[PDB]
Image: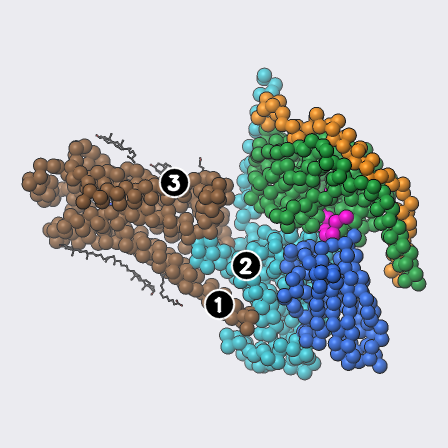
Chain colours: A cyan, B orange, C brown, D blue, E green
């Protein structure tokens, strides 16, 4: 059969072309680290996106650090039901969870953020996905604590018994109350993340501002640490 | 508010659904059995075909 | 006593079984095949199997019989194969350590792309060919025996026993250069790479420990792993190479028993390697579990 | 059909005590973690407390722990919330919420605006 | 005034329940006691398709029973020749987060969609020789979960906005909108005659929709958890659904109630996809436990297991002729069983 053999030859040529294209696409894809950006509507997620850049369902931003390409996806124009479409981001390098640390009292959105973080951490499909916890709006939190408007003592009764960890490294000129509140908020999420105790994924809290210029560097460092920890665990080093 | 309109729409939908004709479950089971038996002779997955007949060999 | 054949045979069988298990686990597990890193372990397993199938049995025959009926040509061929495969295994270990160091410290974010097929092919070629320049090329031409021929005749025949036995004599330049190429430079590279790995792992573990203490309901793992690996490698190879360096300077007065013990300690490395780089890897653990379950 | 209903409510003076009952049917109660959420007039839905499948693990929001108590009975297929020492701000419709899937620790969308596996709740008013 | 309507609604629900109970003269299991069991069913991998970089989430079989379209979250919508394994096409999607794909009955067009809120239609045999987006369908406010072609011009799409819509490809407008679902709609299934389609949703209910009338004719609430998959019985008088329940259930349109439930103690994970054989005797469902369990539609027993996947099985499909069944999974490989 000559016609059949010619058809198979044409199909094989098309297959080879498609395989070459897919090899190039695989090469470019492996060089990219995908990230998922999540947070409350009132959080500084939009400000962070604008800073990094400087009604589609997914918004993507292109940014490169140390000649390393990163794809950050902002889930917009989506309903509040996350238990289904969140599964699509199981293979992302990390999930950047932005929390308004100052929203402890403004309904207390901090509790909702903590519950969302717990749900993300305990998801079956996200067990291998690290979370980059950005405790945003630090300036507002410090201003409210200093001004006396803060009432976290009763919103979170564990605050009274809580004390500043010795490992804390407050910035110069930082009021002790501000440091205590910041580290209490951080430990609130660390309790949820540390509870698993599996080592497959880790949380990387950071005290960041809405217009902070180091957010890109923090993300790069978090991704590098995640990859290093994954490699170490693979070789039984962690 | 839209809540009352949604409730009215749901009630109307329930009314429309309720007034449908329904057959006995036994008749549906018999129809399913007849369909399965009639087409059981043309289901390669149900009964494996000879290796030569299967194009994947 | 002749009972020693049981120990040698058991070691050979264990090494062969470990290498075959590693190879079949890599092949069976489609997840392992697609990873470029796993190829280095496959090459190391192949080298260890070659050692256990073309070096160890001949050595066991030599010791148990104390006779060499295959002639000088086959004595030289055996010695060349032994040196080739030993240096290949050592180079495979060194390159595995270097690849791990690269992936962890150097370019973790673009490690998957940097390990192009060309890089893997070049590193495996370096592992398999460089040994040829020191194992076959010098030994076949007898460059290791020039200047020490009269010494060779002294140990060639213990006329109390008429049996002739194959020997491997190394002169000062050949001994020094081959030892430096095969063990010392690779050993230093492994030491540096594993020290950097230890530093990185210690830093990561310290961060993890601080976070865990902060989040408590109220670091030694990497050190242990690296210590085990390096201790195994040292106890396997370092005594033999130290003896090789020092033996020529002491008029080759080292007793044959010590040389034999160190040589077999070197051979045991091929049998331990399957249980080190596969047992201490999560993917290899999963592959072995699947293979056992079948 | 997954159906959740609540009982109890009405006017209660500040500092009083009240008990909520959540009647569940149409699904295996023991295999789903239950949650209580409330929506005050003009405000969004706020999570109150959760109860594990076996009830061994219990947690409450910062402003509710100790004051309230959540309990479940897998035999009668009912969930309870002992509301003790009600504050004036506690006035809200308390919804008996079920987690979306069984055997899963994650309970994402209990506080969602249009969740489907929620109990509709009873109005609670705290005033003199 | 709100409460007065709710008494009416509860009375209607009770009346529907009573009618369904009255119509339940006998169960399918009881009548099915004296039929010949199917027996052991064995299937192993026949063709392994490789080339996808990320997890596969959806697939569909062509009418010719030879071409296969697979959707991966890496941005590639590859078309495979099952008989020869050759990759006919490799379409680079605009958005990498694709959650659905569909093959037109004539094979002239291919549709796909996902988190991008847009269902892209691709022409495979343009006179220019290349593959290009014929038209993009926009208007949804959620995530596209499933889509199926009624014809080369009409396509039914499901979205995460809890509404399904019928689209006219030529004009790109919504012919009709379905808004009866309260939860997230996850899957669609077209009847053999294309007159009606059933859509499963996260509200643990399945609704039968009339394409032309733009309404749900019936509603089913057998499942207790989110429904992820739905598939019509080959005759079109019944359908099966997959859910997080870890169990499969069968419903009949005429009976308007559940007939059979497929469950087993060792199965506790969710169900991703469900499909029926040509005769409908075998019910094949994909599970999150990395293997697919073959269930007898009548005997309510497991006939076979397809454990050739190393990750979550996200999609399942049976050829029109029923010769083979192709299953996709998160491991980035497609397995064809026979
Ligand atoms: C199962 C597959 C994927 C494993 C691939 C690993 C590669 C690196 C392995 C598999 C077979 C190996 C080859 C087997 C045979 C020899 C002959 C020897 O004199 C030199 C090395 C050489 C040439 C090996 C090189 C490395 C090799 C090619
Ligand atoms: C576990 C071992 C025994 C597996 C078999 C190893 C094979 C390769 C070994 C075992 C015996 C060996 C042979 C022994 C005798 C000689 C004679 C010599 O003049 C040429 C090589 C030759 C012909 C050897 C070739 C390699 C050989 C065949
Ligand atoms: C990585 C490469 C450089 C490794 C190869 C090193 C080669 C060049 C080394 C290893 C052993 C060395 C030989 C060892 C013995 C002697 C005897 C001396 O009287 C003349 C040089 C000569 C013959 C050396 C020549 C160079 C040599 C062959
Ligand atoms: C052939 C002979 C010389 C080889 C002997 C191996 C020696 C060099 C090895 C064995 C144990 C090693 C030490 C083990 C770990 C430590 C701790 C830290 O401080 C890094 C270096 C140091 C101190 C190593 C130095 C090198 C070392 C001492
Ligand atoms: C990594 C190294 C340092 C580990 C230690 C290896 C030791 C056991 C080796 C290195 C040098 C070796 C010595 C070298 C010289 C001789 C002289 C000989 O007439 C008796 C054995 C003796 C005394 C050897 C004994 C074993 C020895 C001490
Ligand atoms: C003399 C030493 C030569 C070394 C050659 C190294 C070859 C590198 C191979 C890289 C992985 C190849 C994977 C495919 C294997 C196969 O063809 O079955
Ligand atoms: C082997 C070369 C690289 C270095 C890797 C091994 C480093 C050894 C460190 C020795 C000190 C270990 C102290 C552990 C204390 C503890 O158990 O908490
Ligand atoms: N069995 C040790 C073979 C070997 C490999 N490399 C060497 C270097 C020098 C030496 O004498 C011997 C060797």
Q: Quadrant of the C terminus of chain E?
A: top right
* Cα–Cα span, label 1 and label 2: 14 Å
Q: Residue at x 30, y 38 (%)?
A: C53
- Residue D90, compared with residue E117, is above or below; it is below
Chain on which label 2 sits? A
Question: x, y percentage for residue E219?
Answer: 82, 47
Left or right for E46, reference E241? left
Q: Nearer the viewer, mark 1 or mark 3?
A: 3
Question: x, y percentage for residue E254?
Answer: 84, 39
Q: Secondary structure at mark 2?
A: loop
Question: x, y percentage for residue C82?
Answer: 25, 41
Q: Are marks 2 and 3 on the same chain?
A: no
Chain on which label 3 sits? C
Q: Residue at x 64, y 36 (%)?
A: E303
Q: Pointer 1: what residue?
A: C209
Left or right for C67, reference A29? left
Q: Nearer the viewer, mark 2 or mark 3?
A: 3
Q: Pointer 3: what residue?
A: C20
Chain on which label 1 sits? C
In the image, which residues are magenta?
A: E222-230
Residue lying farthest left?
A: C160
Q: Are marks 1 and 2 on the same chain?
A: no
Q: Earlier in the sequence, mark 1 or mark 3?
A: 3
Q: Which mark is residue A201?
A: 2
* Cα–Cα span, label 2 and label 3: 34 Å
Q: Quadrant of the N terminus of chain E?
A: bottom right
Q: 10 Å neighbourhood of mark 3: few (<14), some, or many (≥20)?
A: some
Left or right for D61, reference E45? right
Are discs 1 and 3 less than 8 Å apart at CB? no
Left or right for C180, reference E286? left
């Amino acid at each position: 059969t000559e016609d059949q053999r010619n058809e198979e030859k044409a199909q094989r040529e098309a297959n080879k072309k498609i395989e070459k294209q897919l090899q190039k696409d695989k090469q470019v894809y492996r060089a990219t680290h995908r990230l998922l950006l999540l947070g409350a509507g009132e959080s500084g997620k939009n400000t962070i996106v604008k800073q990094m850049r400087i009604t589609s369902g997914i918004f993507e931003t292109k940014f490169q650090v140390d000649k390393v390409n990163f794809h950050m996806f902002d889930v917009g124009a989506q309903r509040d039901e996350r238990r289904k479409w969140i599964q699509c981001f199981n293979d992302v390098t990390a999930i950047i969870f932005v929390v308004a640390s100052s929203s402890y009292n403004m309904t207390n959105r901090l509790q909702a953020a903590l519950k969302l973080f717990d749900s993300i951490w305990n998801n079956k499909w996200l067990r291998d996905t690290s979370v980059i916890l950005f405790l945003n709006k630090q300036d507002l939190l410090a201003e409210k604590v200093l001004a006396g408007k803060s009432k976290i003592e009763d919103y979170f009764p564990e605050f009274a018994r809580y004390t500043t960890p010795e490992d804390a490294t407050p910035e110069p000129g930082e009021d002790p109350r501000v440091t205590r509140a910041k580290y209490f908020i951080r430990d609130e999420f660390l309790r949820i993340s540390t509870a698993s105790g599996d080592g497959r994924h880790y949380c990387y809290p950071h005290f960041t501002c809405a217009v902070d210029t180091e957010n890109i560097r923090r993300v790069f460092n978090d991704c590098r640490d995640i990859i290093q920890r994954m490699h170490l665990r693979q070789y039984e080093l962690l | 508010t839209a809540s009352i309109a949604q409730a009215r729409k749901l009630v109307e939908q329930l009314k429309m659904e309720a007034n449908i004709d329904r057959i006995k479950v036994s008749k549906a089971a018999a129809d399913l059995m007849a369909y399965c038996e009639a087409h059981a002779k043309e289901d390669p997955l149900l009964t494996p075909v000879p290796a030569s007949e299967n194009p994947f060999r | 006593k002749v009972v020693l054949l049981t120990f040698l045979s058991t070691v050979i069988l264990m090494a062969i079984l470990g290498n075959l298990l590693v190879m079949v686990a890599v092949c069976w597990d489609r997840q392992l095949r697609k990873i470029k890193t796993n190829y280095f372990i496959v090459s190391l397993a192949f080298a260890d199997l070659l050692v256990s199938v073309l070096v160890m049995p001949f050595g066991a025959i030599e010791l148990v019989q104390d006779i060499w009926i295959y002639g000088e040509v086959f004595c030289l061929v055996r010695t060349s194969l032994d040196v080739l495969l030993t240096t290949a295994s050592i180079f495979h270990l060194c390159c595995i350590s270097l690849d791990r160091y690269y992936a962890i410290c150097c370019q973790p974010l673009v490690y998957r792309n940097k390990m192009t097929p060309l890089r893997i092919a070049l590193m495996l070629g370096g592992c398999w060919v460089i040994p040829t320049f020191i194992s076959f090329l010098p030994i076949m031409q007898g460059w290791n025996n020039i200047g020490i021929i009269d010494l060779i005749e002294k140990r060639k025949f213990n006329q109390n026993s008429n049996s002739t036995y194959c020997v491997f004599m190394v002169n000062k330049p050949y001994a020094i250069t081959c030892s430096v190429v095969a063990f010392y430079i690779p050993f230093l590279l492994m030491v540096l790479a594993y020290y950097r790995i230890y530093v990185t792992a210690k830093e990561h573990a310290h961060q993890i420990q601080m976070l865990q203490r902060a989040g408590a309901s109220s670091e030694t793992k990497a050190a242990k792993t690296l210590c085990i690996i390096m201790g195994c490698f040292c106890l396997c190879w370092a005594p033999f190479f130290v003896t090789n360096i020092v033996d020529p300077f002491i008029d080759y007065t080292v007793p044959g028993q010590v040389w034999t013990a160190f040589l077999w300690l070197g051979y045991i490395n091929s049998g331990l390697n399957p249980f080190l780089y596969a047992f201490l890897n999560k993917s290899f653990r999963r592959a072995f579990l699947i293979i056992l379950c079948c | 059909q997954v159906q959740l209903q609540e009982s109890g409510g009405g006017l209660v003076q500040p500092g009083g005590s009240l008990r909520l009952s959540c009647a569940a049917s149409g699904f295996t109660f023991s295999n789903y973690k239950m949650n209580w959420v409330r929506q005050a007039p003009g405000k969004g839905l706020e999570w109150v407390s959760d109860i594990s499948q076996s009830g061994a693990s219990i947690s409450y929001t910062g402003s509710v722990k100790g004051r309230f108590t959540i309990s479940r009975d897998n035999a009668k297929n009912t969930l309870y919330l002992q509301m003790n020492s009600l504050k004036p701000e506690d006035t809200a419709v308390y919804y008996c919420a079920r987690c979306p899937a069984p055997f899963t620790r994650d309970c994402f969308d209990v506080t969602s605006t249009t969740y489907a596996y929620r109990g509709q709740g009873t109005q609670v008013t705290v005033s003199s | 005034e709100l409460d007065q309507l709710r008494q009416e609604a509860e009375q209607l629900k009770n009346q529907i329940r009573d009618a369904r109970k009255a119509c339940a003269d006998a169960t399918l299991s009881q009548i099915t006691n004296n039929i010949d069991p199917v027996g052991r069913i064995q299937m192993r991998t026949r063709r392994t398709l490789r080339g996808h970089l990320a997890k596969i989430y959806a697939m569909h079989w062509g009418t010719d029973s030879r071409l296969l379209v697979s959707a991966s979250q890496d941005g590639k919508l590859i078309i495979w020749d099952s008989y020869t394994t050759n990759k006919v096409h490799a379409i680079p999607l605009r958005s990498s987060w694709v959650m659905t794909c569909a093959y037109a009955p004539s094979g002239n067009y291919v549709a796909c969609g996902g988190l991008d809120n847009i269902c892209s239609i691709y022409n495979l045999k343009t006179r220019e020789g290349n593959v290009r987006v014929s038209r993009e369908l926009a208007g949804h406010t959620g995530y596209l979960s499933c889509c199926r072609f009624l014809d080369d011009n009409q396509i039914v799409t499901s979205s995460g906005d809890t509404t399904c819509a019928l689209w006219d490809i030529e004009t790109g407008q919504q012919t009709t909108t379905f808004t009866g679902h309260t939860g997230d709609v996850m899957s669609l299934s077209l009847a053999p005659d294309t007159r009606l389609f059933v859509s499963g949703a996260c509200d643990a209910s399945a609704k039968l929709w009339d394409v032309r009338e733009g309404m749900c004719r019936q509603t089913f609430t057998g499942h207790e958890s989110d429904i992820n998959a739905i598939c019509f019985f080959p005759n079109g008088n019944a359908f099966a659904t997959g859910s997080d329940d870890a169990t499969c259930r069968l419903f009949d349109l005429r009976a308007d109630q559940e007939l059979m439930t497929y469950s087993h103690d060792n199965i506790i994970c969710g169900i991703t996809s469900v499909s029926f054989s040509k005769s409908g005797r075998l019910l094949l469902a994909g599970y999150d436990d990395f293997n697919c369990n073959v269930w007898d539609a009548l005997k309510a027993d497991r006939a076979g297991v397809l454990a050739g996947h190393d990750n979550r099985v996200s999609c399942l499909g049976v050829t029109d002729d029923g010769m083979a069944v192709a299953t996709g999974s998160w491991d980035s490989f497609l397995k064809i069983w026979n």
